[PDB]
Length: 220
Length: 219
Ligand SMILES: O=C(O)Cc1ccc(O)c(Cl)c1
Ligand SMILES: O=C(O)Cc1ccc(O)c(Cl)c1
Image (cartoon, helix red, strand yellow):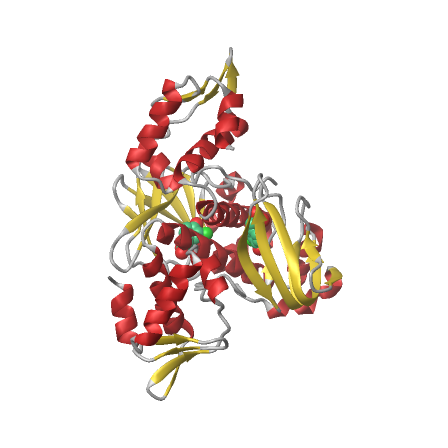
């Protein structure tokens, strides 16, 4: 039931939707193919059976921004028109199941519990983006990066001896896109955290050596 | 079925939940009272029967930001813990109806259409805040104000002679809360639009005198 997310990746997965694929439409996408083409009117929820999708918004002038990444058991909630132009691409071989409104009605008639899993996925999304707007309007770029590391550590960090490890590949490019901070700032902040023996951001994991100092710095 | 919103006010209203408030819990709030107290854990959808609520987020340092305004038939979607500290206050005398998960099961067993109205309400919120993040990362403060005015005109400007009128009280304060732009920028932009005979943002209405020019300046 917990609908917090720290990064916009794998928002509240619903693995149980796999039990209802007969009620929807299976569609596959090779790496690089468009799951949602720019300008395409989507009126389906799109369940990712396995794979990976990058989901962006496109503005009227052609500029493009990351919204989120989605993996196995993720759900794209675009049942109705929203007024946003969306471009979603497969990052690897991807199988999806598309559920129209009518299809979903058959799902919920079979399994009431599915309604609430979907609410939990929408809610996780609203809480994520609503907080992010507010944080962007409150905290400077360096503080947003520190808050991100601190939060990630408290949500996903597992203590291995005298330290915490967060097992995820979080690229500097991805940090930039998620925080809306320019690359020199990202590199400099990450480089000082490593230098001062607080946190080392590696390719495959983040190691936090001093969580109280990271917290303390994030609060300045 | 349209799940757009230009301003964080009266997100996708659900009038038909009025039909089911006997399945929920009616709670009344006086003007100035906390509908959602700071620190309060909420596990109900909260339907606004009548009145008005200002709903804010509060950070660990006690700093606070507007998320939205809600009026009659609005829905607060806080059925599960989110990890955000939320503070919601009644701006007028307010009647609400609180729907637990259990109460919602009863609603949906009765009328399956309510499922989908709630989906529309959530989808409208996601689309609003996700777009706002991306725009904040795309467009400078002044262009975000212009875009706000042009999109409001396009969606609900009413033609009156050579003008378009947007009938709403939208304060300079609220313009800054919505756009994330500081007051001195908001005042200078509004004063320049008025100077240049493009747009006059008055107290209870906004008049657009040159739409094509506003369109152009926003781009
Ligand atoms: O389509 C939109 O405007 C925003 C959006 C994108 C992806 C999602 O999964 C949702 Cl719920 C909304
Ligand atoms: O509770 C939150 O973290 C965000 C929030 C606030 C109000 C709402 O109606 C929703 Cl759906 C979410």
